Image (cartoon, helix red, strand yellow):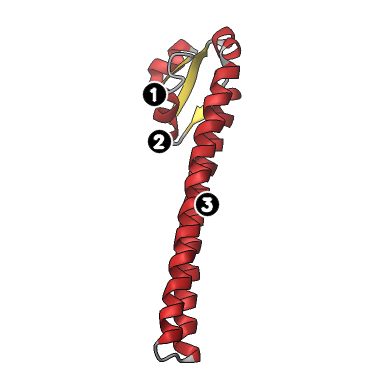
Amino acid sequence: AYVITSVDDEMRHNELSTLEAEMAVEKKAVEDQRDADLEARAQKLEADLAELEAEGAKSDVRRKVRDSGEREMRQLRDRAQRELDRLDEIWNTFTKLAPKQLIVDEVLYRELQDRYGEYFTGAMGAESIKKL
């Protein structure tokens, strides 16, 4: 696991307003997609169940198609929610970033590296302990 060896408090504070803005906009951009994908899928559902209404319809057949559509929609929302939870995790970890903290998640650390990598430093192994 990685460890936070150093953090720049001034730089984090001075530019905090801007990061918080860019963060919410990205989080909102994901939210717009979620709702946009769900409505298109629900319109597809209503269209498909309508074909079955025009065609021959069985109360049990339509239900499994219905049940199948609700399942796909639940998959779409759950995946979008995971993306949001990860995004909130990135921001929370960054604001509360402090030396001696532990970042066990590989993807999270390098996400903190690409964006915000200039505000802090981290390492692994005895090299990191020597720094602390």
Residue bearing the label numbered 1: 114
Q: Nearer the viewer, residue 114 or 27?
A: 27
Quadrant in the rendering for residue 112:
top left
Q: What residue sits 41% from the left and 80% below the top?
A: 51
Q: Mark 3 vs mark 2: which is more N-terminal?
A: 3
Residue 53 to residue 121: above or below? below
Instruction: Report the Cα–Cα distance between label 3 and label 2.
Output: 26 Å
Q: What residue sits 53% from the left and 49% below the top?
A: 81
**Foreground label between 3 and 2:** 3
Q: Mark 2 vs mark 1: which is more N-terminal?
A: 2
Instruction: Report the Cα–Cα distance between label 1 and label 3.
Output: 28 Å
Relative placement, left or right, of 21 versus 45 is: right
Circles 3 and 2: CB atoms closer than 8 Å: no
Q: Position of residue 88 (x, y in %)?
A: 56, 36
Work out which quarter of the rendered image holds the N terminus and state it: top left
Residue 48 to residue 101: above or below? below
Residue 93 to residue 31: above or below? above
Q: Mark 1 vs mark 3: which is more N-terminal?
A: 3
- For disc 2, the neighbor class at 10 Å (few under 14, some 14 to 19, many from 20) is few
Considering every residue shown, the one lying at the far front of the view is 54
Q: Amino acid at mark 2?
A: Val
- For disc 1, the neighbor class at 10 Å (few under 14, some 14 to 19, many from 20) is few
- For disc 3, the neighbor class at 10 Å (few under 14, some 14 to 19, many from 20) is some
Instruction: Report the Cα–Cα distance between label 2 and label 1.
Output: 11 Å
Residue bearing the label numbered 2: 107
Q: Amino acid at mark 1?
A: Asp
- For the residue labelled by badge 2, is the local secondary structure a helix, a strand or a loop? helix
Considering every residue shown, the one lying at the far top of the view is 10
Q: Position of residue 101 (x, y in %)?
A: 55, 25
Instruction: State the mark number for residue 35.
Output: 3
